Length: 104
Image (cartoon, rainbow, N blue to C red; front, side, top):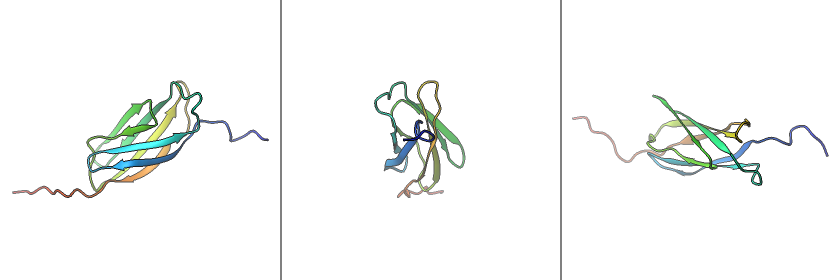
């Protein structure tokens, strides 16, 4: 057929299976299952006060100790050992916490 774009590791189908107030499970689909070995995902969370990050070997990654009612920007970058693909971006919106702090 042709040769140009086809042939590259890119994280697509990035969606949140579960979005809690202080936690959220992330999921994505990789265009490689046969040689899905030595696959690593570099997560980079960016909040408002501070940012976080975590590396996993699975297409999923939950973010503990999260904040409710706050925008978050997660970037899942695939890494098959010594390779670098395209970072998967997915906007998430944590639900409003039914609990509010009472000062005084």
